[PDB]
Length: 372
Image 1: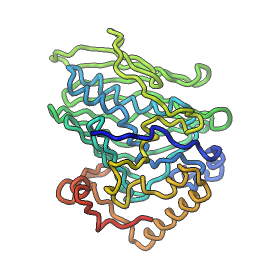
Image 2: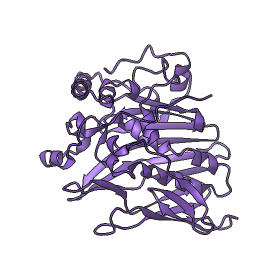
Image 3: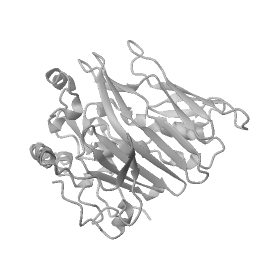
Image 4: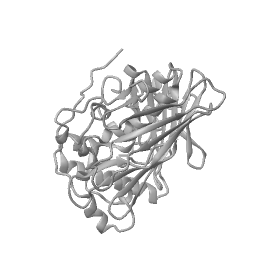
């Protein structure tokens, strides 16, 4: 089957405040814990933002059908950076999810479904489990940030664990470090820095290096990928090259491996959102009447903000934060329901009759409290 998606969002209803303005007043605790006006946000939650990691999920499906899978897994690993191609996207940040807030994403068109939940508040920890007939991916992540004096370093702490359900081959990697520049003056923007590697359980390794730029060459957009197969294997060494803002190709054959999709119309007025981003917070026939009380699509502050009702969005943002603080101080914080902690910095999807997907089949949410 299929569903018609909006592929668009209302234009931003307010001008973007300056992040630096808040950094100077909160010298110490960074962003995630700082009381920010709703105007500093974009209309999605962090769970929805991280779900964009799967915008190009078909690359994973293609990987399970190719002899050199790490080439496509590498493309997939780098692809998420493309959401920042329109610098407008770097002006605001997603809403901080509430503890126990969830976000499901079923994309029949790409053959996968994803479920996510905020499993810890201090520090923030988000758990993700994406499944396709031929692959699945787990991720326990904690976003982090540290200003270097003029620029801020952004990182997602946690290993993305991909598993081919066809062969069992595993791939792992930590998302690359990115930097937010021009916080003082000019047009703010983000760019990846340093390098990172993707590792296969079969020995293969991929080394991704981003071009260095920090004084003239403008925003760094290019990168190179060196594929190194293990010895005694029939796979050979290969190199890939491209720009995370546009495409990636095999340097030897010049064959295109990945290309960016579309942004919404007039993106400068719509947070620089991709069509995929614009579709994250939409309730379609897929979700209607099937969501637990905790889905990000049900948050009133995000919804009001999306629809341009700023004053109401601010009031709701404060209200949700206040309700959570009250629950917390009483020692009555809500416990996550769909993931279980297996170790330090590692959560795992709970299977069984009370799993998210099993509950969804029968609207079994009677034991799920209303966070707002």
